[PDB]
Image 1 (tube, helix red, strand yellow):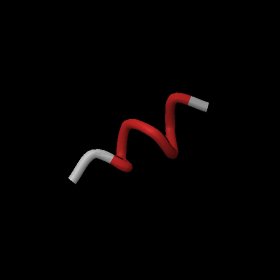
Image 2 (cartoon, helix red, strand yellow):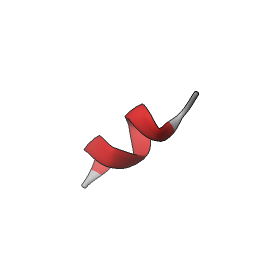
Image 3 (cartoon, rainbow, N blue to C red):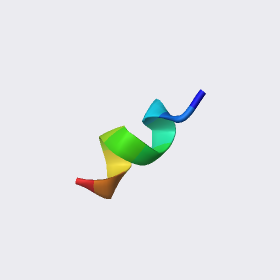
Length: 10
């Protein structure tokens, strides 16, 4: 539910 922020932040 949060990987969307992880995979994009970089």
